[PDB]
Image 1: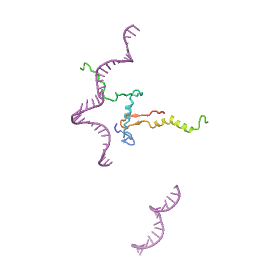
Image 2 (image 1 turned 90 degrees about the vertical axis):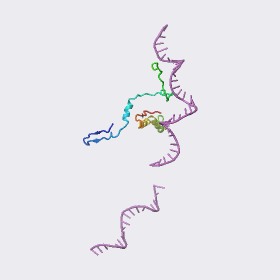
Image 3 (image 1 turned 180 degrees about the vertical axis):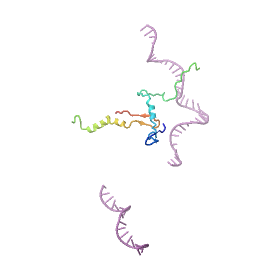
Image 4 (image 1 turned 180 degrees about the horizontal axis):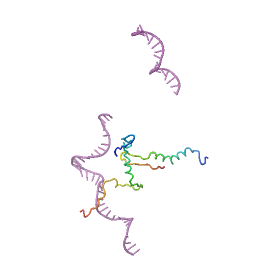
Amino acid sequence: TAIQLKLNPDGTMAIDEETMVVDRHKNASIENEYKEKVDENPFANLYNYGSYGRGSYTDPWTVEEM
Amino acid sequence: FLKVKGLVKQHLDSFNYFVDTDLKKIIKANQLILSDVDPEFYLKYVDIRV
DNA sequence: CACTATTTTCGGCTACTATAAATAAATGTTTTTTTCGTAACCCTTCGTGGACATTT
């Protein structure tokens, strides 16, 4: 995403007006487009006391690992 | 004239045009709230109802 | 009627959640200073005449 130039027959070795600065949003835009589009039902985001907390469930141990 | 089209025409038919159509021409001119930090965030207002 | 099978349920596994102590050190988190409308009328300007000095 460096600075680009051009060969104009009128003005040779001229610098272009648009790539002087960067948008910083077009590369973010394509990142968003291949994302999953979900329709929210108010019962999905249900939270309880076991929410926004530490920890997980450890896999129950095996005789191989004993 | 006054049966179909009464005496408070000028007040009733103005607010009723604001609610129906003239809200959707507002959010369509203030859509896409954006942030510059973390540029992959966008919230857009699609339609509005009362 | 035999068993398949999601449903119902037991069940135990796990993992902190407070409550008191030792440090000790690292870490972030938030206040208190230290500094970067008409009408007078003053106001402003263009200007015109007086006398002085050099020069003919």
